[PDB]
Amino acid sequence: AANKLIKEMVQEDQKRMEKISKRVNAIEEVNNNVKLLTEMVMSHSQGGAAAGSSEDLMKELYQRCERMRPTLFRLASDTEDNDEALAEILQANDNLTQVINLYKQLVRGEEV
């Protein structure tokens, strides 16, 4: 109902929750995309292939990966007093930079 000044509290609870949940969804999405793109890139590393639709899916996964870095940068500037959350973010960005590295190699003839 109509209330006095304890609206700062339910609104704080709300920001706590949104913050954590956005982190979770980001990290999960990262973990998922990195793992599959990795799996796929390796398999096309002169072994089992598909081309066509597979080229399409690796491309999409690659673009999603590029798109998540900005997202992680923005999440990391919102981790006031939680170095643990900040660390998870930073490890996830590392997973992303890395995978965006294999894809690129795969796409332009390199090894590894």
Image (spheres, helix red, strand yellow):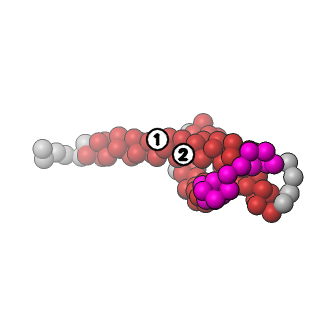
Q: Neighbour class for label 1 at 10 Å: few (<14), some, many (≥20)?
A: few
Q: Position of residue 79 (x, y in %)?
A: 54, 46
Camera-side residue of 24 and 101 = 101
Camera-side residue of 102 and 50 = 50
Q: Which residue is mark 2?
A: 29
Query: Does residue 99 appear to the left or right of 70 in the view shown?
Result: right
- Tell whether label 2 touches label 1 (CB within 8 Å): no
Q: How many marks?
A: 2
Of all residues, the one furthest to the left in this rendering is 1
Q: Position of residue 98 (x, y in %)?
A: 74, 50
Q: Which residue is mark 1?
A: 20
Query: Does residue 43 appear to the left or right of 110 in the view shown?
Result: left
Give the vertical position of 110 relative to 82 (above or below): below
Instruction: Please name which of the two marks, 1 or 2, marks the residue nearer to the observer.
Output: 2
Q: Position of residue 27 (x, y in %)?
A: 56, 43
Amino acid at dot 2: Glu
Query: Does residue 25 appear to the left or right of 88 in the view shown?
Result: left
Of all residues, the one furthest to the top in this rendering is 84
Magenta segment range?
44-57
Element on which disc 2 rests: helix
Q: Is residue 83 magenta?
A: no
- Using the rendered view, name the quadrant where residue 12 is placed: top left
Residue at position x 31%, y 42% in the image: 9
Q: Is residue 47 magenta?
A: yes
How far separated are the C-alphas under marks 1 and 2? 14 Å
Residue at position x 60%, y 56% in the image: 53
Could one spot residue 49 in this view of the protein? yes
Amino acid at dot 1: Ile
Give the vertical position of 67 relative to 84 (above or below): below
Could one spot residue 98 in this view of the protein? no
